[PDB]
Length: 166
Ligand SMILES: CC(=O)Oc1ccc(/C=C/C(=O)NCCc2ccccc2)cc1OC(C)=O
Ligand SMILES: [Co+2]
Image 1: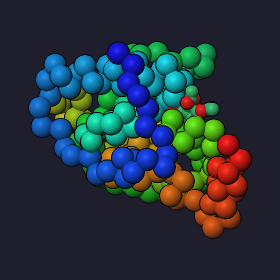
Image 2 (image 1 turned 120 degrees about the vertical axis):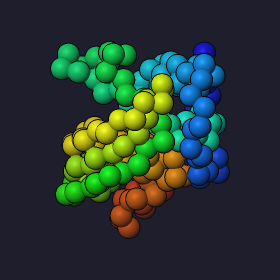
Image 3 (image 1 turned 30 degrees about the vertical axis):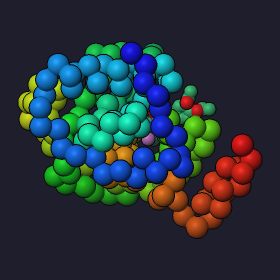
Image 4 (image 1 turned 90 degrees about the vertical axis):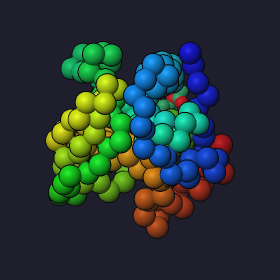
């Protein structure tokens, strides 16, 4: 089922999500609803709090060569934790909870994370570029952080201008 997407400046997006402890049918349905919700709004990443669920889980489904998304490559990361991070790069980001606004944010160009899939299986994943950016962006949501929070002095002003624009 489709779930309501929470938009900035809702205080709900500042929540610190909690670890998932029961990987059951209920959790799986929330993940399915999240995927259905992300696609319907044409996003490539979505954190649980963006739909009102203060849980430490998020999904990422980057499009392939053809430019289309295949539910097969969808990553479901629960209880993530950074093992290592390195480098630095700028990436223009967007967010379903801040529709209509896109701005460059500084991110690590490489990260290694540890997490669990929907079946509680432990995984270790190394990522770079786009995938590494999505991971950092989504994980920020779990800690109540939005990418507009990480904007430089100037860009923050541009955000306010464009915000007043809508
Ligand atoms: C008007 C407009 O274009 O609004 C949108 C803005 C962003 C998005 C999607 C953003 C998104 O998936 N971000 C994932 C996290 C990420 C950040 C940077 C690089 C990789 C991954 C969708 C929109 O469409 C609707 C219908 O709300
Ligand atoms: Co986001």
